[PDB]
Image (cartoon, rainbow, N blue to C red; front, side, top):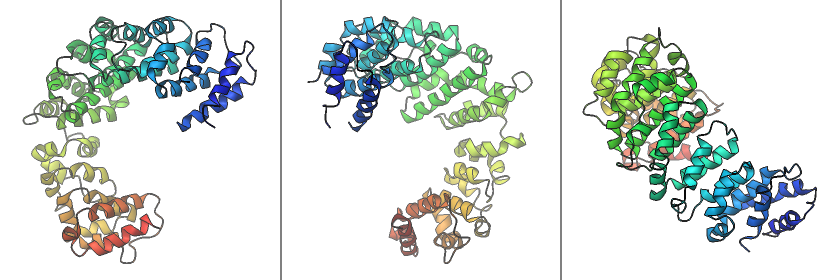
Length: 452
C-alpha cells in the first residue's frame, strides 16, 4: 500500500541466497513507484550495483527504476550519505554498468545544482559519454539527463567549459561519428544556459572546412545542419543576439552545398527538407534589413527559378522577406486550393504579404473545396486579426458555411472538427463587439462539440 512494498523488497535483497522469485517482486515495486526511514533501499540496492557477480534472477531494469524514482524523490542529504562525492568517483570509473547508471541518478538531482563542481565528477561523466567504446544507451541517456539538469548552475557550466574545454574541442576536431554526434546534442543543451562571455568560439562554432568534412558521413551532416537550425531559434527565443556574429558567415556554406548537385548530390537527396528549415531561420533572424539571407538567395538558393521548389519557399521562408523581394512569386503560384494550405499558413504571418493575395483569394473558391480543406482554409484565416477582417465581412458565404446553414458537405469528419473547432474558438476570442452578427451562431456551433 505505502513504503511497505519497497521495505518488503529490502529484506529479500539483504538475503544471502535471494528468493528466486526476485524478478516478479521487482515487477511490482517499480510499477507502484510510478504513483509518486529515508536511507533503507539506497544502501540495500547499492550492494547489487557494486556487486561484480552477474544477476540473471535479479533483472536490474526494474532495480535501477526503483533508484531512478527513489533518489530524486527522497531527501538528498540522506542520498548524499549513502552516495557521496567519494562513492561516485569509484562508481563512475568502475566497469559495472548498473552502478554507473545509478551513480548518474545521484549526480542527476545534485542539491545545490553546483555541488559536484568542486570535484572532477563532471570530468569523469564526459570521458564516459564522449567514448565511442561505450554503447550502453541506458547509461548514455543517464549521463545526458544529469548534464542537462546540472547545466542550470553557474559552477557546472564553468567546469564543463574550462577543465573539459580541451577534451571537448579534441572530440570536435577528431570528428568520430559516435562521439561527434554526442557533442552536437550536448552543445545544443549547453547553449540554452551559456551566457555571453561563457561562449568559447571554437567548441560552439564549426568552420567551413569542418562542415565540408561532415559531408563524408551524411548522417553527421544532417545533425550538424540540425545543430545550426536549433542555434538560430535559441537566438530569437532567448534573445541571445550576441551569438549571431559567431555563426553568421559559416551559414552561406550550407547554401552553397544546397545549390551544388554535381559535386554534392547526397546533400539535396538526404537533407533537402532539413536544410530548408535552416534557411527559414536565416530569413527570420534579426538583421537590418535581411542581407545575410539575401546574399544566400541571390548567389546560391535562388528563390523561384527552380520550379519544384517554389512550393516549399512559399511554405517555409519568412513572409516578411517574401513580400519585400518576391511579391510576384507569392501572387503567381499561391491561390485558394487544397495544396496551398501550407502556403496560406506561412504567408498569413504578415499583413502586407496577406494583402498581396487578397485578390487571388475569393469566397466562391473556398466553397468548392471539400469540407476538410474548406475548414483548413477558414482555420488558417482565423489565426490573425487582419485575416478575420477578410473572412467575417468580405467572404460571409464562407463564414455561413462554417456554421453550416444546413451543411456544405456532411458528415464524416476524421480530423476536420479540430480545424472547425479551432476556427470556432478563435473567432469567439475576438468578443461580441468584433464578431457582430456572428457571436450567437458561432457560440452555438462551438458548444455542440464541447458538450456533444
